[PDB]
Length: 147
Length: 148
Image (cartoon, rainbow over all chains, first blue to last red; front, side, top):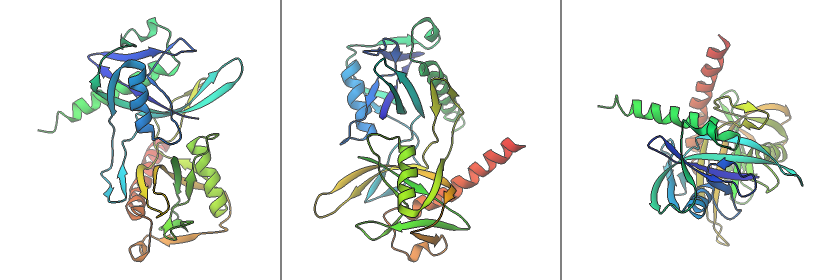
């Protein structure tokens, strides 16, 4: 079962939302519908859940042609377990790094990335955040020795 | 509408099948069922289409515990446009690099990378194969440095 998520980090803070059933904070995201792409689903769901409009940004090799466009690589992909009383799901999670490009905050909270252990968070959050800091740290670094 | 393909390379040869409707050669793959993960889908389709059993492989960080396990990163992800004068689809194609673990070639052709340019391939297949080769090299070294 395909799902997609958005990691938005601005000024040491990550935007998170409460899961309507689990209650723990999660990266805004959700089920990738059939007739849509994971890129469209993450944009659509980030905005309906938070009010913020984002754009997934990742690495692409640069492959271009009239018949196909390359899409950004996710920050990571996890098969996560979710245990409901009626049943257990496995979610194939395409976790994208995202950027804000519009909207207005309506739901969700900016959680300092250092206080992530002071709140109930979906199991992955802390692991994914570390991965995201590293990556941003690297990119910031490499974006250094460009000159 | 997301689909998945596997790229199997052995002895300077990539395994390609003929597109069901386009005829052109493409790597094996197909639509991902609601009921399955892209990883399960690629093994299933490859299975059906070639008879060979394969295992997706790729870059990972190493995340794994009781609550979640990381899956390998595709080789490349192309959002392909497929014009059948009779519809016209858009395919979010998660393309994985895969290795052989069983089964047996029942259908399909081994395409020598040295002849690929004089062969009718589905758009960008040649670009992707090139990526596979370099990518395989990089996973080769990650693997032997890890072996050291």
